Image (cartoon, rainbow, N blue to C red; front, side):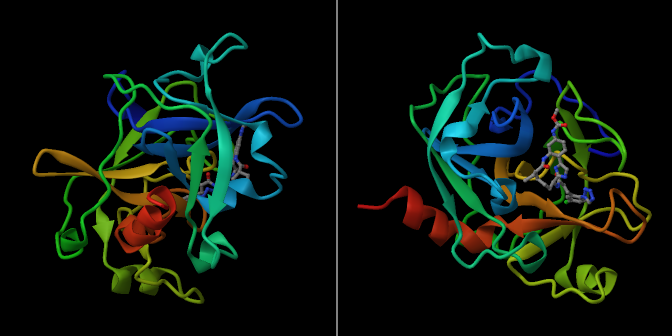
Length: 238
Ligand SMILES: CC[C@@H]1CCC[C@H](NC(=O)/C=C/c2cc(Cl)ccc2-n2cnnn2)c2nc(c[nH]2)-c2ccc(NC(=O)OC)cc2NC1=O
C-alpha cells in the first residue's frame, strides 16, 4: 500500500495473507474470507502454481512476524480460476480457494459481505484498500497490514486514464487524480472494502495499475458485484 497507515488488530478480519511454500515460504497475495471454507482472491496470483499443495492461508494476522513454522494456517483443497481469465489487464481476475478445513469465526477472522445485485446502483464513499504490499515501486513486503482510504472512480474517467486499455464494467477503479494513495506489489488478491449502512462490502479485488499511486493512474480492481452469480455457482454447487 502506498500512502497508507498501520491497521489496528481486528480492523479487516476478512483479510488473509496467502503464502506459497515453493521454493521457500513467502507471502504471495492478499485474499478475503467470504465463507467458512472460501477465500476470494485474484486469478493472476496462481501464475506458475502447479498444485494447491504449496499454498497456506493465514487469517487473524496483523503482522507478518506472527507467521513461523508453528503458526497455524488453512491448506487449500482446490484452486478455482474464472475460465474466461487470460490476464489481469483483460479482466476476469477472480479466483476462489476452497479450504481443506473450516474457518472458526471470531473477532480476529470473519467473512466480508459480497455486494448485493441491488447495490450496483449505490455510490460508495468509504472505501479502503488493505495489504502487506510495497509502499513504493522498489520496496519490500510490510510487516504490519496497511490501509488506505481511496475514492471510487467512474468507468468513463478510468477509461480516459488508461488509453490503449479496454476498461470494462467488470472492472472498478479507485484513486486520487493527484495520486499518492494506492495498492502496490504484494497487495493483489486482497480486498477493496466499502462501508455502507454500517455494513462492509467486498466491492473490489486488488488487480492492476500502471505503477503505484501515480497521478492520473487509478488502481484497477475486479468489480465483485459483477461476479456474485459466478461466486454462488462455485460456492453453492449441488
Ligand atoms: C504470481 C506472483 C504474485 C502476483 C504478481 C502481481 C502482483 N501485483 C500486485 O500485488 C499489485 C499490483 C497493483 C495493483 C493496483 Cl490496484 C495498482 C497498482 C499495482 N501495481 C503496479 N505496479 N506495481 N504494483 C505483485 N506482487 C508482487 C509483485 N507484484 C509480490 C511481491 C513480493 C512478494 N513476496 C515477498 O517479497 O515475500 C517475502 C510476493 C509478490 N507476489 C507475486 O509476485
